[PDB]
Length: 309
Ligand SMILES: Nc1ncnc2c1ncn2[C@@H]1O[C@H](COP(=O)(O)OP(=O)(O)O)[C@@H](O)[C@H]1O
Ligand SMILES: [Mg+2]
Image 1: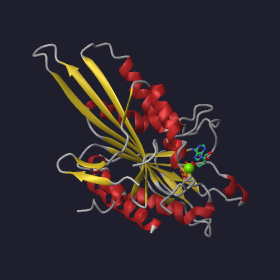
Image 2 (image 1 turned 90 degrees about the horizontal axis):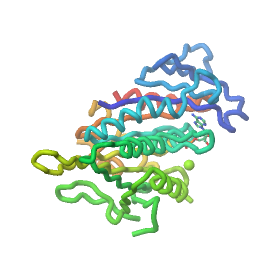
Image 3 (image 1 turned 120 degrees about the vertical axis):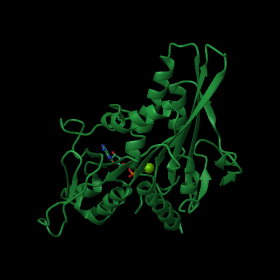
Image 4 (image 1 turned 180 degrees about the vertical axis):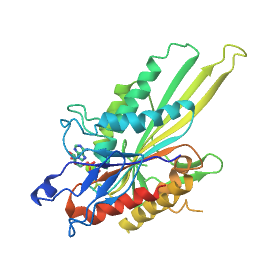
């Protein structure tokens, strides 16, 4: 239950101008942060399921690639989805640590993130299915959560509000749910999505997929369904606006350790009630700046990820 990894990125323009010295090191699954003031102060140590070293470039033999990331976490999380269970992955961290590049990624030199890959993989396993008793259905929803109003990142309007249907549970009223029938088609929705995103990387991006599996039982001749709810999330840069963000992340924290009465405590948390916990495995990638100038925020992140256990 619950899976946590951290990923340090390469220096960015800012850090580079700031000569920002690297204060992060990694040894398997142990990211050690060094304090700036005290170059000695022995690097502080933490230990996760995964500690990806992406400080260099796709060149360095020892570089955690978007594939590696997806193959370790995504891949499995997708597998469980086929088994019939809900799945949710989370990107969390300072703005610019790497959440988006990790979830979505890019295109050239195929730097596709977890979402693009996971998708391609989901459809690849479906099309190669050679049992006529198995038919599939993939419904997608994409959105943004700001000041706790849901923005349909793949549509116009009608601000949306998340209710709590009697039995069914949480849901965003009037939120588009499009059935796709191929990777490409699901890829357009992605591009259109990250395209609509303008805003200010201050809101949570929730890419949900409702994977349905229909099995035609040779005997009895009864088609039974099996529904999985995959929710890939790009959280806010942790670091009124702050109120909803802080409350969200917080509520989320006292859950991972728990999952391994806090809930309606916030929309984001009140929405993934079917993914946050109850059951079904979740995962959490933590973007980390390798720059000294971010010591406090970088450290705070680590602690947040360390508490998720
Ligand atoms: N592991 C990485 N490999 C390559 N570039 C990265 C990596 N992590 C971050 N970056 C760079 O940093 C920038 C910001 O990452 P991003 O995920 O978009 O920010 P945020 O934390 O605000 O979501 C990108 O424009 C990208 O080039
Ligand atoms: Mg952005």
